[PDB]
Amino acid sequence: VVFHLNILSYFAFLCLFAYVLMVDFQPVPSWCECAIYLWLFSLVCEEMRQLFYDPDECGLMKKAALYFSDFWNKLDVGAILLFVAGLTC
Amino acid sequence: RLIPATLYPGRVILSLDFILFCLRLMHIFTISKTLGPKIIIVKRMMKDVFFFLFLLAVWVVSFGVAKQAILIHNERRVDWLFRGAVYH
């Protein structure tokens, strides 16, 4: 259920994102807009939990190549860099 | 059906009884030699009925939300904007 509660949070965040493309098409940070900035702060800092999880205690750049060895990890941050190309518009 | 102010919910809740009994119609139709031994393959699939439905129809939603967004659709009613956004 820590899997289930994470899924339906992620199942309904895209529903929350579906709210702010249909009706809430405004050029301002609105009421139902500010949480997505706090939602993007919430999940990419779980990689911060994983970077400090189980490393070697001298290699900071030699552990991150394993995250570079995951194309789904590059599909995670690749869906972050497109949001920086989407928030700036 | 006996309560007179609820014929419109009495029109929509009993049409599923027509097909819930049609599962019971096919239930006694596990008989024929080309039917019986291969209606057991759908018995290998009855929970898996719920599988690919919940796969593909939720995967339908991955298109069905993705369709209306870029174009400026404007057809809305009370329970027909759901038509012009979701049912289409």
Image: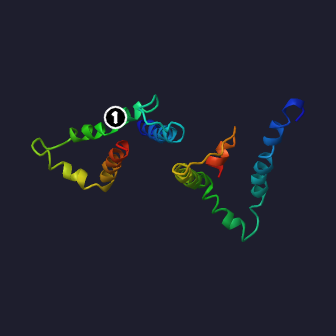
Q: Between B87 and B1, which is closer to the camera in this rendering?
A: B87
- Residue at the spot x=77%, y=60% of the render? B29
Q: Between B70 and B66, which is closer to the camera in this rendering?
A: B70
- Decide if residue B56 is on the left or right side of residue A79: right
Give the x, y percent position of residue B11. 83, 41
- Residue at the spot x=19%, y=52% of the render? A65
Quarter of the rendering occupied by the C terminus of chain A: top left
Give the x, y percent position of residue A5. 45, 35
- Residue at the spot x=63%, y=63% of the render? B41
In the rendered image, which residue does mark 1 sit on?
Answer: A42
How many marks the image carries: the answer is: 1
- Residue at the spot x=32%, y=51% of the render? A78
Give the x, y percent position of residue A19. 51, 38
**Amino acid type, label 1:** Ser
Regarding residue B3, the answer to whether it shows in the image is no
Extreme residue in the front direction? A27
Give the x, y percent position of residue A43. 34, 38
Which coloring applies here? Answer: rainbow
- Decide if residue B66 is on the left or right side of residue A52: right
- Decide if residue A32 is on the left or right side of residue B74: left
Q: Quadrant of residue A3?
A: top left
Tell me the element at label 1.
Answer: helix
Above or below, comparing residue B29 to residue A38 in the picture: below
Regarding residue B1, the answer to whether it shows in the image is yes
